[PDB]
Length: 440
Ligand SMILES: CC(C)CCC[C@@H](C)[C@H]1CC[C@H]2[C@@H]3CC=C4C[C@@H](O)CC[C@]4(C)[C@H]3CC[C@]12C
Ligand SMILES: C=CCc1ccccc1OC[C@@H](O)CNC(C)C
Image (tube, rainbow, N blue to C red; front, side, top):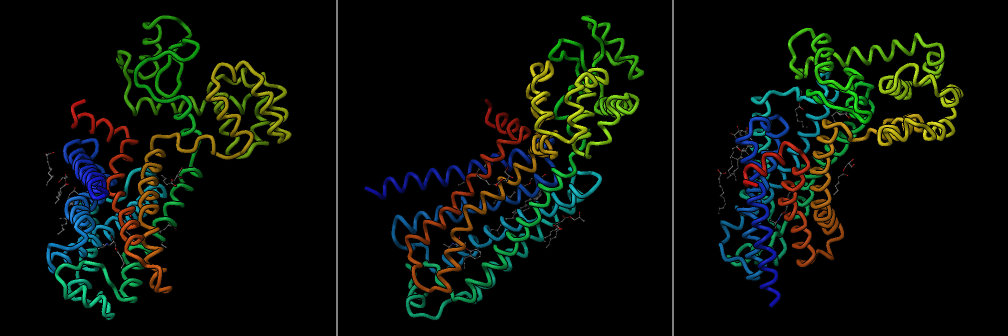
């Protein structure tokens, strides 16, 4: 009766992997906005999962339920070679993603890959050619084969497909195929998360706090705004707001502006906020006493409220100058501004308290993209590392291997081929593609 329940659960795992990855591949294959360098590697990853879901996981399920191998010794060696290829290719692709994200964040381009689609295609094809060679040749040439009697009996028997390996292979294949790219991926992507946080500036901080709209909108007070929190007029007239817009840009806008035009106004307003601080006798000394991070928090306040407005916080500024952060924070919380925009205020106040970008952590869309890619990496590790740790331990220790524990932990890694599509539901671009392909 256990076999029935086990059979259903296993069928749904197969179905969840297949449609899940087919959906992801179809989304990148058809939607123009999703044909990026990062998404080409995501396709390489989704292919390995689809291959795992169609050629590995179904035959694995059959081996458990029938308690025997009914496909012969040739498909057994081939099946094992494909499985290892899928794991090796999946982790090497995740390592490439990490290295590519590093080179991007360390470049002036910041979020765009330095690789071209042609180069990325070659990188992907080289990963599969190398992973194919490292995974098929030691299995086909029988370099993996153990010398103990129980293994030889399993090799000769056409109804035995128990992955018996010699200690050397179980160490060599594990290091080259998994541990080496994992160590590099974890070490490199921790630096990408570091650079994203360290390279956070006032412009990024304000694009988070104010947002971006190329259409005229009303703020909390009700004043007409455009771009990144650029107030057009205090007048309650759309024509009055459109006139000030046409005058500022220097063309017939009709209430709509370009991304290039939005950045133009933004660089002007930020520049005006910094200029205003230096001409203000009450803000200029506070600006000098502050560090790089806390200067942005003061520029942020002058951007939102204005030179005169911020200069009104005589008590708060005094303690910012005296470097008494926690004390300044209470007086900043005890204000009209904190009540008006509490989410934005809390962030700026935390910046003044901590002196770090911790409040603006993964708030930018480009930063959320790094988090999404970081989740994909982290899950793969949590799913495969227990199998690989218990694998390398039962090589040195020799005992406590079991079949029950080995297959179970291998299936923890198998279930991962169905998780990646669910994690892509974080990206709005993928979400928009999925609902279109599913007609919702
Ligand atoms: C089991 C073995 C024999 C089959 C392996 C499947 C191979 C053919 C698949 C898996 C991953 C695939 C790649 C995934 C990513 C891309 C990006 C896309 O923009 C062009 C094609 C390209 C470069 C694919 C080519 C074919 C590919 C290398
Ligand atoms: C020899 C250790 C296992 C191994 C090493 C390197 C790369 C992949 C590896 O194995 C992944 C497993 O999914 C294999 N599963 C068997 C075929 C049931």
